[PDB]
Amino acid sequence: EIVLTQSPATLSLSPGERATLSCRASQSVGSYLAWYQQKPGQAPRLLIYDASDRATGIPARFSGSGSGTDFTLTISSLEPEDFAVYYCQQRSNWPPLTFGGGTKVEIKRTVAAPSVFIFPPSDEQLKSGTASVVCLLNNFYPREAKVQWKVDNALQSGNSQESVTEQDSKDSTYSLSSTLTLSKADYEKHKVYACEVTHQGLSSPVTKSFNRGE
Amino acid sequence: QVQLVESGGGVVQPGRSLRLSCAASGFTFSSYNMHWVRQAPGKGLEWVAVISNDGSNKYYADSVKGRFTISRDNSKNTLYLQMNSLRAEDTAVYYCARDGRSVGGFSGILDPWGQGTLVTVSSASTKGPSVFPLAPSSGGTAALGCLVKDYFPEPVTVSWNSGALTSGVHTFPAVLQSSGLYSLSSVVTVPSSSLGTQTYICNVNHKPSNTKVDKKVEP
Amino acid sequence: ETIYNTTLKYG
């Protein structure tokens, strides 16, 4: 199949700035390259087809160019509604029709270090027989962050799950929640529960911890 | 006025079958080839299948060959996707999309797309959540929340103080546990000085199980 | 409406 590679994976820009998105094909697709926009919570929408032709009703700020293996999508001046995900798609050699992996256009802002909070399992949950420890990283930017769980100073790996909010509508930050899950029996075998947070806005990692039963 | 409306998505057990429908309006359905495309949670777009205007020419992604069948009923303006031997990896929103008009074949231009229908491949049974407090631990800012644990299927909604509290609220995407049940947290940051005076209640609604919970969260 | 080039012929 034709492999399409989109770079960068994330573009961080301010409204009103020019946006340039790249798509590269593993072999020539001629001009048979289209671009789709996917806004949060919506289906994709055709923007550009045949490398450079705007679809019906697409504003003039969207343009495309390229042939062979190298293509670009340009938004001359970003509007608020343009912060979205963009996919390229080739129709030169198919089946299968193939898509690039997508480029997210996000709002750029100043670096913000997370505020960190740790929550022990509730007594209510412990009565039911399980223990969830939660670590919250609140309102940080950019989205790259690392959570390291430690249990009596043993680094935990593979036994936690995390998720991240979409960019905040007011301050353009992200937030992250991580849950470490243990049986009640294993939870009661250890004392010190710690969430260690690394982020480029922190001069050194921030650790929030508690001692079980205090 | 071209419109495509998918239906039929739901929970289906691994190895079982499900048929999706796409109802077309606002154009001459029999004149157009039609596609299915899918999008796994948090992932990109994957083309699934195409069918010619008259139903005679069909093609499929390698990942669904031998398991999925595309078909259409032009008299009913409906496109179908019969999905057999479903696998966890088939979990996705499924979109129908109209193939751009061309002479003598398929174009491979997808325009427009429907709103999608969600297929969840799972052995889990419907189960309402347990709702546990994330209790606040200075003249500064405190965090508190609700852990909405062990429910199935998605989705759940969470509000705070019946919608009166929205500033500083973060309700996170659920995660799928190895049990096959989901877990979600919803938090809010508030003034530490408010903890003795202000009541904080998270309002959880898991509509698939008709389960509503109002959970007061106290220090 | 737009008429596109065919990229996959019918059988």
Image (cartoon, coloured by chain):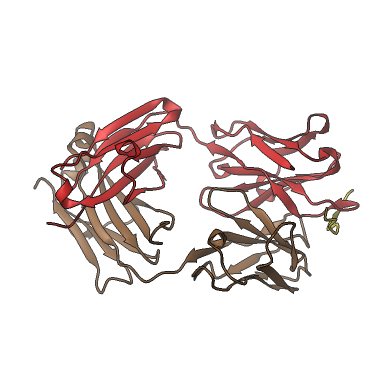
Chain colours: A brown, B red, C yellow
Q: Residue at x 41, y 37 (%)?
A: B156
- How far across and down, in percent of the image, does residue A210 sit? 15, 53
Residue A190 visible in the snapshot = no
Residue B79 occupies which quadrant of the picture?
top right
Whether residue B165 is visible: yes
Asked if residue B196 is positioned above or below residue A66 in the image, the reply reads: above
x and y percentages locating residue B45 in the rendered image: 62, 53
How many numbered marks have been drawn onto this rendered protein structure? 0
The image shows residue B37 at horizontal and vertical percentages of: 66, 47
Residue that appears at 70% across and 44% down:
B65
Most distant residue in the top direction: B210
Occupied quadrant, residue B68: top right
**B91 sits to left or right of A208:** right
Which residue is more in the foreground, B83 or A55? A55
Residue A129 at x, y = what percent? 23, 34
Q: Nearer the viewer, residue A4 or B142?
A: B142
Quadrant housing the C terminus of chain B: top left
Residue at the image position 70 percent from the left and 40 percent from the top: B4
Q: Is residue B156 above or below residue A206?
A: above
Name the side, left or right, on which A25 lies relative to B206.
right
User: Could you say which quadrant of the image residue A16 lies in?
Assistant: bottom right
Viewer-side residue, B31 vs B82: B31
Query: Can you say which quadrant of the picture contains the N terminus of chain B?
Result: top right
Identity of the residue drawn at 31% across and 33% down: B130
